[PDB]
Length: 80
DNA sequence: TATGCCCAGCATCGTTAATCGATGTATATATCTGACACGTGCCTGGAGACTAGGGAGTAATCCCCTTGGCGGTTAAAACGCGGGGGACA
Image 1 (cartoon, rainbow, N blue to C red):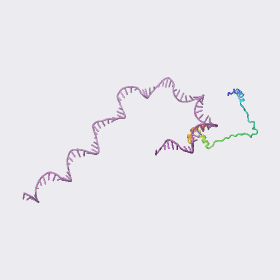
Image 2: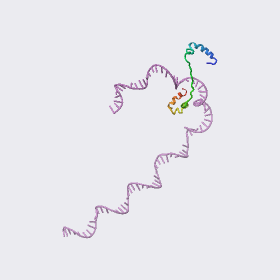
Image 3: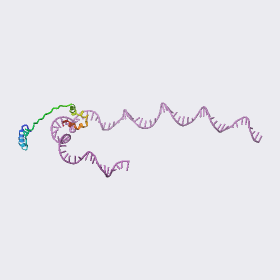
Image 4: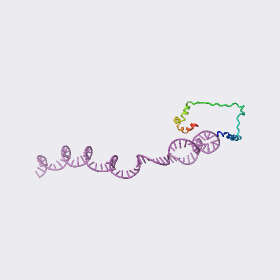
């Protein structure tokens, strides 16, 4: 928490938490097992996509088509 | 003397014209009532003007409450089948 008490803080947290804790990496049985890997994907927007990336953040053509439902999903659509 | 013949005589029918009166239609006049606008008079309940103060506006922060997402059971909704008893004539 505190910037300069943090050492004081983990002096209390590291010494106490460990017992009832176990931290151990794979570095085991993974030597046989074939390798792990992950790739990201940058996909840019489409045609009908912007329409509903742009119009949805307002109630322009989101209210023209399915306007009755617009109301409940309006926040649903925003950040979730 | 009785019976056909001459000379009036009012009522029968119809038609013309003047007259009192009823009906229909204007036409300018004298009431009837029902006013709505104005001036008469007066009251003050509003308008007009100024003040003083505290409500309410707004802005800045907080933190609680409302919405959300998710997944497990476990009751509830859903369905149908069947036949009885209430609706309806």
